[PDB]
Every structure is written in structure tokens, then in C-alpha cells.
Amino acid sequence: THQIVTTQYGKVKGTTENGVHKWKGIPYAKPPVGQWRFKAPEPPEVWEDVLDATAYGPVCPQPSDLLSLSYTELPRQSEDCLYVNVFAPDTPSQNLPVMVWIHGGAFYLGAGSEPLYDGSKLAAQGEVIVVTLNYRLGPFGFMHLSSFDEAYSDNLGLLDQAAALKWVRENISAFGGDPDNVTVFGESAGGMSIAALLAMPAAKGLFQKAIMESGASRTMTKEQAASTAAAFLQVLGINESQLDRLHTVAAEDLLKAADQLRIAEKENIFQLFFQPALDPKTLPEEPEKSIAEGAASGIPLLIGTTRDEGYLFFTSDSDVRSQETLDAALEYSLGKPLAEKAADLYPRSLESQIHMVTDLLFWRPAVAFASAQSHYAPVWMYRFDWHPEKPPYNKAFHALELPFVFGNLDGLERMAKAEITDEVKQLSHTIQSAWITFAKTGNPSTEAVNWPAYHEETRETVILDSEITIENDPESEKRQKLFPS
Ligand SMILES: [K+]
Image (cartoon, rainbow, N blue to C red; front, side, top):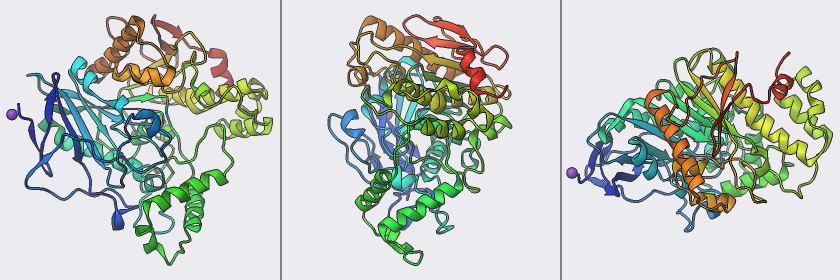
């Protein structure tokens, strides 16, 4: 019970608190600094002594936008941030299911060690092992420089995630987990990351189940990645013959250059900037297309969205964008005729731009991905509708389901100033129980919900709220407008 575990790179020692074994700050890669900046993750150097794993490692450098809201006491920031944390229930049971969390944050914010993602409650209540991790963000993980040097890798942040999953496959049995029953789950950018991981060469065979919360196929073109990369170096004053400077410039300067590029670009309604990029070596094609062709055959998928995603993207006082902007977003998302028709579904207004974000950034992608995967594996869909009744937090905002999934309800106070009532505790128990049962069997059904499989003929969907219900082909009129006739 003293919790010393031998990893492939050396021994680590954790602790036990309230029935949960915990190991924090375990290195899964060599710190991506200096010459290793902008390169694929390398194995960390081995150590012969016992590494103290009772404190979280640093988080990736980033603006304080999310950290200030997520933490009461800000964490240390460093490019040396590639660490995983393990939470396991103190039980005689072996070969436990493993749930690996990929945090959201628009690919430039967040950390696996944010208070909201503490896996103690999930591990204890479900008797599963929970793994959280950090991956390179912003200019460190999603600045695709392959166009300047083949030695550099694009989609660095995704490669870090894959490296962490590889670490889990090779080391989790030593922590009491089943390396052959690994469920990867994530929200927002984390869900979008999982869409990519389900198709990436780097992640082949590294997990057996997936949960995608408010996130699906999302990428920028190879051309867009290259143009942004060139603009980035220009801001830094680095020439094609001064690439060595990319490994010496201060991290703070990389962040400043990144922030400078954003402000220079008129913000879009989806607030998209950093994101995965198409690249022959790391992400050959759009995740949705790859899944539609069977790249994730046999991998059960639990996927969903919140009813009011878009309300977190605007304020009642936000400016109303032009019709041309909305039509541009429609063409981008939909296509040629799909944009033409159904365009009348979003007449200029604050309401329409809110609905467009919910529909085009989250709902349509989720339905498209779920439908595609339904031909190759069991799929289960949900729509989260819960929220406090009193304004102004009376909307099922993007990310509002997170406190329920992890069981860390203090997060609801900062997200919606909501009180932890019996209804809230009950809903968290129901949602967490479903996530756990899915990790264990590939079917999210519980005593509170007999979940119907999602397929294109009936599109049966579970509605998560104080009272669980099922809707058959929800928002059918909207679906018919957003998809080919
Ligand atoms: K022991």
C-alpha cells in the first residue's frame, strides 16, 4: 500500500487519500524545450531512483484567461509540462477500465490538472482508473511549421496526446488498469482532438472506446497552416535562414507573437484560431471522412452536445454580424446548395448567430460524426439540457456538463453560480454512472437510463436533465435543412 510503481522510465511513488491512490506529475515525454521545441514528443530520460509523484507538474504557458477562472491559486507555467496524473480506486479488483481525459480550451488554454478535472470522485464511485494529462498548447503545440523544416512536426499537441495514450498502453497495467480497455474522453477542443485521434496514424491501436463531448471533426487546411506559420515567423522577425532562433526565443515572446496574430485577425463567430491542421504525416485527411470510411471500426462511441452551446459565445450586448458573415460561415460549414437553402434559417440577429454557433460548430458536426461511425461501431448520442432556472445563467451553456461528469460540483458555482441541490447531485450521479458503465462495457445504460443505440434510421437520442427522456430524431426539421436532400 505504499504506492511505488515502476514505469518504463523508472519508479514513481504516490499516495492514498480517502480510498483513492494518486500519482501526480509523472513525466511521459522529454521536456519539449530548446532543440526539442516544435518537434514530435521524445521519450523522457530514464531515472534510477524513486520519483516523488505527489504534486502536479507545470502547465503549458498560456494567457491567464482560463487559469484565472479555473484556479483559486494559479499554477506554475513552463514548456516543461508533459506530465500525466493517475487516480485509482483502492480496491482488490484488477484490470480496471481506464478513462483518459483530454481537456478543452480552444487549443491554447487549459490543463489536465485543473481542479475541475480531479479524478478522485470518478475513480472512487466507478471503480475505474482516471488519467489526466497536459499537451502542448497555442504557439507551442498548434503552430504548424512543417513548411519551414521537415524536422518539425505539425499537430504537436495531438502528437503529445497520442504519446500520453501510448504511455498509458505501456504502463497502466502497473497501476492496476487494463491496457486493452482504455476509453479516451474529452470536451470542446478535447472532443475535437479525439475526432482526430480516432483517425491519426500516431494513435492507431492506443484506445478501445471514445467519448466526445461538444466536439467533433475540426481542422484548418494545410495551406492555412502554412500561411499562418509564415505570418508567425514574420512577427518574430525570423527568416528562413534564421530558424535556429525558433529554439532560443523566449516562451513569452512566442505567446506575444501568437496574441498579436489573433488581434490582427477579425474574430469570427466560432472564435476559432488554433486548431488541428491537415498534414500528410500527422493528419492526412478530415477526421469525419476517415471515420466515414471505417478508420475507427469497432470502437464504441458516446457523443453529444448541450442544447445551448452558443450562449457562451456571445453576450446580450454582442454586436450583430452581417448576413454576409453568416452566409460565409454557412458556405464554409455546409457547402454549395446546403448554404443556399437553409440560409433562411439564420436571418441577421443576435439569436441567429448564437444558433449558428450551436448548430454549425457543435450539433451538425456531432450528428455527422455519430452517423458516420454508426456504420462501423455502436454509437450512443445525448443532448444535455440542464441549467438553473434563474437568469442570466439559465442556459445549457457550452461545457456546463463537465461538473456533472467529474462530480466536482464546485465548478457549477463558477460556471453558473448554481447551488448544489439534490437534483444536481442526482443528475451528476446519473451522468457519471453512464460514463462509467460505457467505459466498462461499451454501453452507457444504467438503472436510470436504457440507452438506445444511435443509427441513421431512427436517430434515437438521450436527453440528459433532472428527468431523463428520449427523443427520436430530435430537431428533425433542422437536420433536413443542414444535410443533403
Ligand atoms: K506498498
